[PDB]
Amino acid sequence: GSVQIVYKPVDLSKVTSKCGSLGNIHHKPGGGQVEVKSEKLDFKDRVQSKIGSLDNITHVPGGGNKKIETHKLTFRE
Amino acid sequence: GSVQIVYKPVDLSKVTSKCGSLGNIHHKPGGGQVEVKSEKLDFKDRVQSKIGSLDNITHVPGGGNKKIETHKLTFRE
Amino acid sequence: GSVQIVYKPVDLSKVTSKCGSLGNIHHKPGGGQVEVKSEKLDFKDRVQSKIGSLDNITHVPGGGNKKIETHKLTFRE
Amino acid sequence: GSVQIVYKPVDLSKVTSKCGSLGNIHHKPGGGQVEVKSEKLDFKDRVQSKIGSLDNITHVPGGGNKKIETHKLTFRE
Amino acid sequence: GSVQIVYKPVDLSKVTSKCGSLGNIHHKPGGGQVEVKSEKLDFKDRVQSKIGSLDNITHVPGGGNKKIETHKLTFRE
Amino acid sequence: GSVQIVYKPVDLSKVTSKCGSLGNIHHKPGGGQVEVKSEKLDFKDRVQSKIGSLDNITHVPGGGNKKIETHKLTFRE
Amino acid sequence: GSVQIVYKPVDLSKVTSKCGSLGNIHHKPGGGQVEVKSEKLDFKDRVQSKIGSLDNITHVPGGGNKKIETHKLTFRE
Amino acid sequence: GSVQIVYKPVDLSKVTSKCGSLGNIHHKPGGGQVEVKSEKLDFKDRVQSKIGSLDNITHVPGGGNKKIETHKLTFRE
Amino acid sequence: GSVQIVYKPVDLSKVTSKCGSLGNIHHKPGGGQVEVKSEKLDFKDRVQSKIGSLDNITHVPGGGNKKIETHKLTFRE
Amino acid sequence: GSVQIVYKPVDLSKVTSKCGSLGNIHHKPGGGQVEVKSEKLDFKDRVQSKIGSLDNITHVPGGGNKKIETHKLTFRE
């Protein structure tokens, strides 16, 4: 028996934005205190650990539009 | 027996936004105190741990529209 | 016996927004105190743990429209 | 039996943005204090650890639009 | 049995941005204090560790649009 | 007329204390938030004002015995 | 008329203390937030003002015994 | 008329203390945030002002006994 | 008329202390943030102002006994 | 009329201390952030101002006993 598979998705999407003016932003963190304690650490896989951090991030993108698209075709016999 | 499969999705979506003016934003964190205690840590898989953190984030995207689209076709025999 | 499957979804959706002016935002956290205690931690799978955190987030997107769309076609024999 | 597979996805998407003016941004972190303690650390896989950090990031991209697209075709016999 | 596979994806996407003026940015970190303690460190794989850091980053790209696209075709017998 | 005044107070008081062991004391304040608003402030005398404060005090004296003694003799004619 | 005044106070007081062991004291303040607002401030005398403070004090004197003694003799005619 | 005044106070006081061991003291302040606003400040006298402070003090005197003694004799005619 | 004044105070006080061992003291301040604003400042007298400070003091005197003694004799005619 | 004044105070006070061992002291300040703003500053007297400071002091005197003694004799006619 013959098997025919056609996979023709179509996309014409648009992701736009507009901003006349963007600014005057203040970010003033006032310190902190962090203390961690451990003995053994065994990470053996796709691990993404993060231990004992004091971080400040200022992320101001003028655009910032994100589009994610995944296609998957699995054929088995 | 013959098997025919046609996969033709169509998209014309739009995700837009507008903002005349965007600003005058203040973010003032007043410190803090964090303490953690542990002995053994075994992470063996797709682990995304995060231990003992004091973080401040200011995220001001002028746009910020997000679109996610996944297609999956699994064929078995 | 022949099997025919046609998969032709259609989308023309729109997700829009408008904002004449957006601003004058204040975020002032007054500190805090966090303490955690543990002995053993075994995470072996798609784990997304988060232990002992003191976080402040200011998220002010001018747009911020989110669209999620998933298609799945499973064929078995 | 003959097997025919056609994989012809089409994309015409656009991800745009506009910003008349973008600036006047202040980021003033006020110090901090971090202390970590450990004995054994065994990482044997695709590990992405990060231990004991005090970081400040100012990320102001004029654009900042991100597009991710993955295609996968697995054939088995 | 003959097997025919055609893989002809097409892309015409565009990722653009515009910014009339971009500047007047201040980033003034106020010091800090970090202390770490360890005994044994065994990393034998694709490890990306980072221990005991005090970092400041100012990333202001005029553009900053990122596009990622991966194609994979696995054939088995 | 002759006036004779004799002022011979006598003190032999003792103020003692004993403590075999004194310790293991924890004081962990969890932040706070204070806001004050005023226009005019006129202090012209022995004034001891204190406005808008967030204070923490740990006072652990091993002794701490206090003795106050005042003598006053006023003669008028 | 003759006036005779004798002022012979006597003190033999003692203020003592004892402490076998004194320690193991923890003082961990968790930040805070203070904001004050004013226009005019006129202090013309023995003024001891204190405005807008965030203070932490750890006072652990091994002794700490205080003795205050004042003598005053006023003669008028 | 003759006036005779004798002023012979006597003191033999003692202020002592003892401490076998004194230590193991921790003082860990977790940051903070202070903001003050003013226009006019007129201080013309024995003024001891203190405006907008974030202070930490660790005062551990092994002794710390304080003695204050004032004598005053005012004669008028 | 003859006036005779005798001023013969006597002091034999002692202020002592003892400490077998004194140490193991930790003082770890976690940063902070201070901001002050003013226009006019007129100080014309014995003024002791202090504006906009972020201070840390560790005062560990092995002794630290303080004695204050003032004598005053005012004669008028 | 004859006036006779005798001023013969006597002091034999002692201010002592003892410390068998004194040490192991840690002082680790974690940065900070200070900002001041002013226009006019007129100081015309015994002024002791101090504006906009970030200071750390470690004062560990082995002795540290302080004695203050003032004598004043004012004669008027």
Image: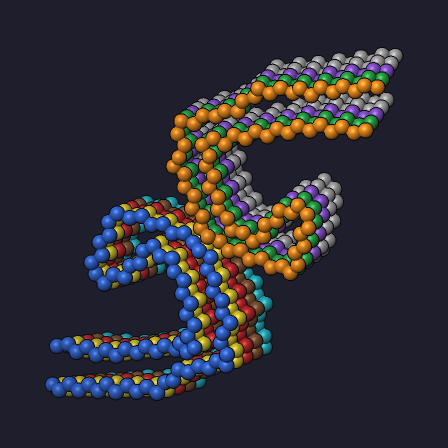
Chain colours: A red, B brown, C cyan, D yellow, E blue, H purple, I green, J orange
> Can residue E69 be seen here?
yes
Point out residue B31 in the picture as x, y percentages from the top left corner: 49, 53
Please give left or right for residue H30 compared with residue H1 in the image. Answer: left
Identify the image quadrant of the N terminus of chain B.
Answer: bottom left
> Can residue A4 be seen here?
no
Which of the 4 image quarters holds residue E8? bottom left
The total of numbered circles placed on residues is 0
Vertical relation: I10 (above or below) E62: above
Closer to the camera in the image, I23 or H68: H68
Which residue does the image show at 40% across and 76% down from the upper left?
E64
Please give left or right for residue H6 compared with residue B56 in the image. Answer: right
Please give left or right for residue A42 compared with residue H66 in the image. Answer: left
Vertical relation: B75 (above or below) J55: below
Identify the image quadrant of the C terminus of chain B.
Answer: bottom left
Point out residue A25 in the picture as x, y percentages from the top left corner: 53, 67
Which residue does the image show at 61% across and 55% down from the upper left?
H36
Closer to the camera in the image, D41 or H28: H28
Point out residue D3 in the picture as x, y percentages from the top left corner: 17, 85
Point out residue D69 in the picture as x, y percentages from the top left corner: 32, 78
Closer to the camera in the image, A44 or C69: A44
Closer to the camera in the image, I52 or C22: I52
Which residue does the image show at 46% across and 49% down from the upper left?
I30
Which of the 4 image quarters holds residue E49? bottom left
